[PDB]
Amino acid sequence: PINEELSWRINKFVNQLRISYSTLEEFVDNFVYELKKGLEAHRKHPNLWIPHECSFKMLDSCIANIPTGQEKGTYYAIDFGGTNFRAVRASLDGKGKIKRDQETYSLKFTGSYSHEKGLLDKHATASQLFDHFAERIKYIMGEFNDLDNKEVKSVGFTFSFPCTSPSINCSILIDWTKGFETGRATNDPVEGRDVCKLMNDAFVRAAIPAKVCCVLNDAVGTLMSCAYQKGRGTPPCYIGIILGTGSNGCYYEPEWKKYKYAGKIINIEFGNFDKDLPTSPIDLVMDWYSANRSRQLFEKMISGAYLGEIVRRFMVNVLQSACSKKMWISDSFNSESGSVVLNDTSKNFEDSRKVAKAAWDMDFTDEQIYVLRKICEAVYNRSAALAAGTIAAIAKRIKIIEHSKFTCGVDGSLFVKNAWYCKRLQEHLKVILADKAENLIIIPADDGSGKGAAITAAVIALN
Ligand SMILES: OC[C@H]1O[C@H](O)[C@H](O)[C@@H](O)[C@@H]1O
Image (tube, rainbow, N blue to C red):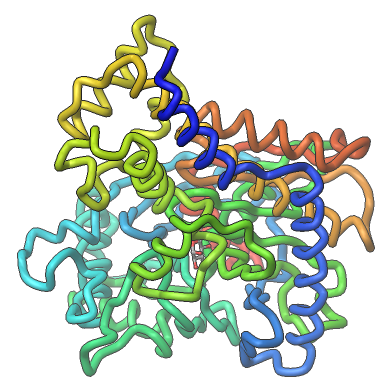
């Protein structure tokens, strides 16, 4: 039970974050419309993204051979998913089974102090990033005695960024997202260059006996892994969703041949959606402070690289002068801390006080811990609601041609590391799909980004 001047603030600011069922429907409609415009735009100029024609990049994956579940072998993969970089080793057993061995390192915290924060810096060169990839592949390879010999090892590469892929072995970086600016201020950029080559050169510098044989977006990797692990009689995987540091999805487009595609699976790049976004003033501020102003706008509303900060800025606006100096500090509250508050089962809300004291140095009153709950609910629900609409809209585009039972695989910290979020996304998704809700099967695909690169390396072997 709370002061009235506070509650008026609570009611006002949560209302900027509400999403009614009618508007969410318009979203699904606007999304589906934007999808066809992307397909038609791709038919006209398949090699070029003309953004005024469509916010979606609708990029060809060059994948036409879906996994059969029988792909066999052991392959290395490198999973470049964003702020963290993860190197993997995976063996395939010939049935839908995967053993996986993984080592997650960080790009922000390289161990240097130049370049402000990270290998993301405009002043970091391209060569450093790809060398660091080879450096960690070297270490994982030496550990397994696979490295020392002189016969070349093939490697799958998931590059979680919008790329133009003229082939499965060719991928040109279009635009950095998720806060990266690597090479933009140097003579050695990543943007506009073949990432397959840049990596193969990183192998060459370190004498590593490896070669990248495929480059794929992390969303498509999730789909590939699901298809491989697809049980007999279990419907096929036609959608891959990543809901994590960034937010994006791939899907199976039946008209792939018609609209001049080489693969069947399209990387939508829906993070860059810009039509009728239900923005709040904090959303304008977040975009303004970004390194990619006016791009990835939808992602800046719903992605996990951004939820904690949205909560914080809303938090400051509601409690007003009761906030500690650290409450005003940018990026004091990450999205993981929001997961704790939403998924708190302690009695005295003990766990929720800890994240508040840990981030802000405030022994939260019972009043203020109530506020942190509601502000976390209002923000996170907006992400889940729009995310469900996104899935449904993708489902509607497929079902327009192909209506049946099929499954959609979901990956990323926001979905597998947050029970509350996973509940809301599925709840909203059940509402939008209406009667057909039973037709879409949501299945978690943990580490689909990393497995899928390896499975793709296998399918190349199979031809
Ligand atoms: O990390 C998941 C998503 O985040 C960003 O939007 C990337 O541009 C996109 O390629 C990726 O699929």
